[PDB]
Each structure stands twice: as structure tokens, then as C-alpha cells.
Length: 49
Length: 49
Length: 72
Length: 72
Image 1 (cartoon, each protein chain N blue to C red):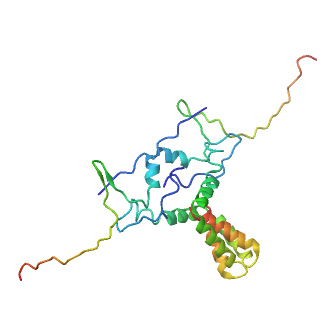
Image 2: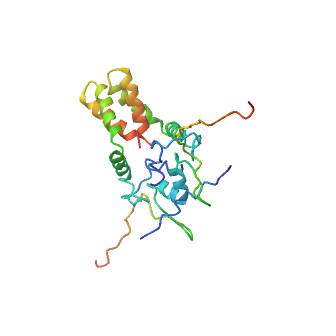
């Protein structure tokens, strides 16, 4: 005989440890990671000089 | 924030790897096990002598 | 979680086929081989540490197979 | 099942917290601890077989903790 094997929703919420959650509801909005920025400041005034 | 974990049903089906399945949809009918039975056959003739 | 401690070596054995034999009878031996062939450098470096720690070849192979077994 | 291979050593870890940091960092040690407190005699036998192999103390302790950590 054959049987189905349940729901692995809570089984895979166990499997997703160590994996950073992002927010995919309306737009694929991540809130993790970084980026490198070169910052050129030749054209900054001082606002008080 | 607080989130629930989800359905633990399929993870429970992984947990039961090594559990002998019985049925209790009607009764509690096991179909596993054994019993030591001393068979004492004194008054057992042949039906045909 | 609940899908670990899988109720395996707890007596209670009979002639009847259990809930998962031939499905759970080889799940560790498949996920270990999949893990090795997708993470080889820990197996090479575990062979280096096992060859280092251990005088005779039996405990070198023993420390190798145990260090390979403990990793997920 | 799929509740194994728990996505632990994969790189990718940023400053942000993961899905179960502080609830998955110690579940392995708690599971092994309650396993030993439910199954002592394999740890006694693991001490005996760990002692007879390993002609120095370090690999006796090493084979002991590995033989403990392999069995669930």
C-alpha cells in the first residue's frame, strides 16, 4: 500500500537555519549584506564657513 | 518579532523511522508481536482411525 | 528538531516491516556521500589530520571515518 | 529527510542574524547530552574501546568524543 508523507513545512524551517531571511512579499527586498563604496569628497562645502 | 514554526507532520514521519505501524481507526488492532504459548495436546485423536 | 532522534535502536523489533526500512535504511549513507562530493576539501584535510594523528593504519582509518562521519 | 542538511557551513553569513542563531547553535549539544543521559552504556563501551586503541591519551579522548558524536 502507498501513503503520503505529511508536510515538510516545519521540517524545512528546521533546514533553513543559518540562512538569512529576506522579505519577498511585495518586491524582493533584501536587508542583508554589504557593498563597497569609493567616496570622493572634492566638492563639499562646509556650511558655516 | 515572533513567528510560528509550521507543520511538524512530515518531520514527525521522519521521526518514526523504526516504529511499527498499527491501526486505531477502529479498535486498537495491533498486527505485530508474539506470545509464548505452551501447547498442551492430551486429548487429541486422529479422526479416521 | 523532532526529525532527529529517529527511534531506531530501541528494541521493539519484529518480523513486520517497520515504518521506514529501505527508505531510512540508507539515508545517512547517501547524504554523507553527497556531502563529500560537494565538500571535498574537508575530506582531504581530514585525511591529513587523520594521517597526522594516529600511529598505526587502523586508528588512522578510524579517525578518518569518524571525522568524516561527524560532519553533517 | 529534508530536515537534515541544515545550511550551516555555506559562507554567506553577514552581520545580520540568521533564521535560528541562538536556537540552533546549541541544539546539537543538547540532543547529544539527553542522548547520553538516556543511553549510558554505549558511552561506557565507547570509553572501553576508546581506551584499548590509541597508544597515547590524546587520541583516546579524541576517539571517545568522536564515537560519542557519531551515534545520535
